Figure (cartoon, rainbow, N blue to C red):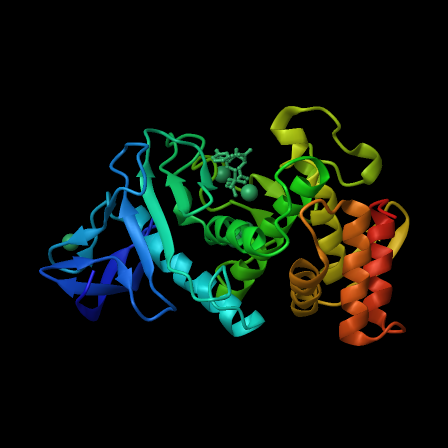
Length: 316
Ligand SMILES: CC(C)C[C@H](C[Si](O)(O)CNC(=O)CCc1ccccc1)C(=O)N[C@@H](CC(C)C)C(=O)O
Ligand SMILES: [Ca+2]
Ligand SMILES: [Ca+2]
Ligand SMILES: [Ca+2]
Ligand SMILES: [Ca+2]
Ligand SMILES: [Zn+2]
């Protein structure tokens, strides 16, 4: 809508207070005009029709329980946008400042989230397995990254390419988490998962096997579930990414960590320059070393660490 840019205040899923960019026109809307072509947050009102209606508030104060998820989706989207802009010099997911849209309160007791090809969607969870998904910054960034991937490499959502697609989302979701410095970790969705059970998480990048995910190419899932295990085999790449950044010894192979920042640069470059819709793990390996090479030279430690990492997860 057309109106006056302003700032509201509200409480997020975790009960934290924060300021949000809104737009004033009769009502106060969850419309952030400060970022690219804007960030829009909608209310799906427990239905499945999208996107629903642009979030309207009467007083610019979002302290109602029903508001929480909207606050977070809106806020975290902004943070994610900033990350891409500040860090990778990317303007929105399309690189052309496309408007970012999210819908919350999707369905009833919906334990998931997704990028529908046009926007982000978040369920509220059943309150047992999950709480409103937008409460996790890694989650929001994961979703937004799916968009980035779509506009770039276009990795098809199945089998190996789909696993890569997933890993990308986990990696960047994690990097964004570190970027915001919000109790950063190498875990996925710990903030909205099992309300419930402390210390747990949906996925682990540092130790995927902890949750039954493969951490070695030899343990790759080859069935048909999960689109051919896109959310499973991602653990392999996730583990690799972890090693590149943090370093360590996995299956007898030692990897010298190069740090988060370099990890991001390397992966972003691979994503945007070398990956294709049908790329596989092995292709991912080549893209990654090519990027590092481009960035730090063939004889660099960076290239070295990338190689060891892939070796460590049995990806040649
Ligand atoms: C919390 C976690 C990061 C959320 C992830 C969502 Si997703 O974007 O990877 C996949 N979402 C869907 O498949 C929703 C249905 C759909 C809509 C449109 C097109 C295709 C599918 C995530 O990792 N989800 C996985 C784990 C769940 C327990 C949350 C999963 O969906 O398997
Ligand atoms: Ca209000
Ligand atoms: Ca965390
Ligand atoms: Ca996390
Ligand atoms: Ca938990
Ligand atoms: Zn995903």
